[PDB]
Image 1: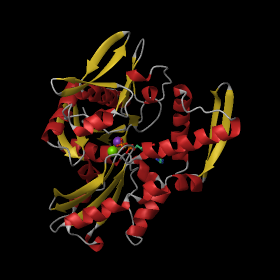
Image 2 (image 1 turned 45 degrees about the vertical axis):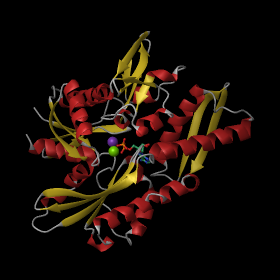
Image 3 (image 1 turned 180 degrees about the vertical axis):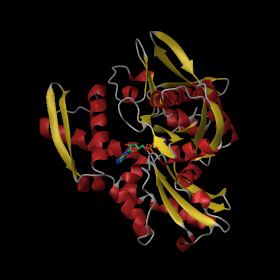
Image 4 (image 1 turned 120 degrees about the vertical axis):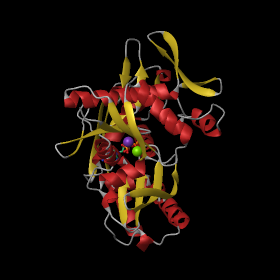
Length: 378
Ligand SMILES: Nc1ncnc2c1ncn2[C@@H]1O[C@H](COP(=O)(O)OP(=O)(O)O)[C@@H](O)[C@H]1O
Ligand SMILES: [K+]
Ligand SMILES: [Mg+2]
């Protein structure tokens, strides 16, 4: 029985398996090759993934996401205190450890972040088993390069809770380099830059690989810049358009905003391959249909400051690594948001036109490398 590779992501997770000699990234039951790291507790069931993220509930307190932001941290951590101010669910203190408290089937329940993450890993395990047709018990799970020992142990604990034997925890940028075979270099140092713009975080890592051995030389980024922020700019744009056209403010109706956010995320993705996207929602607010569109150009304008801001951490990483651009041998794209053409253009221009590694979908590259590593260790 195969071991799998799992990218347990801040916003989206992905699972792959090495078989027939290569990695197959596995689609979930809605046919999506990544799954939101998102749980919802309802009157009658626990929803995980797409069903949780797109649920349109009257009571927003009972969904949980961003557990990776809490994992391995103490309640009084200023990052925890800061993040709590923008989550709809309740974080409580139990012996200086944060727990999330929700109502499920009418009863109050609290969960440690490792337990929430275990539910996401359980879903990914189940996606893999549905595809393989047999049970899976072994996995490699990835984490950010900047995770410390406590965060790594907590991620392994989430794996154990989910019923997995965790063969190894590897760094996300290392996983991406392995996906592209950059581990097979030979004697002599090879410097790899990983540009990872995801749904919630932006990370730039510089790795040196020497005779198969990886060393992280520098990391930089922004833990609050990602695709969700671009979604938010689109949602705000369309809320303004609705008010302009229909003289009604929908922004305080949680159900309308949720439906709009789901439609906006789809439209954003479409703008990565097409030059315009339709946005069509029946009965969005007070019975009023909302049919409209947006061009790729307009989306780029809405997000221009955020896209440009990704270049400073690249300069920082290079400075910390004491490397010139020409000393970087391979550039690798990771993260769903690096599928945005404007983002690729900015990075390519910064690197004087050089080729970017992007043939593996960037939102899948981490799971791909994790799956290669899982096959190696089994
Ligand atoms: N084709 C696409 N174009 C633009 N953004 C995309 C595309 N596909 C996924 N995304 C965005 O990628 C982000 C998720 O990135 P991903 O790397 O899958 O997760 P994480 O950052 O949680 O590891 C989401 O904001 C999603 O909307
Ligand atoms: K991911
Ligand atoms: Mg990621």
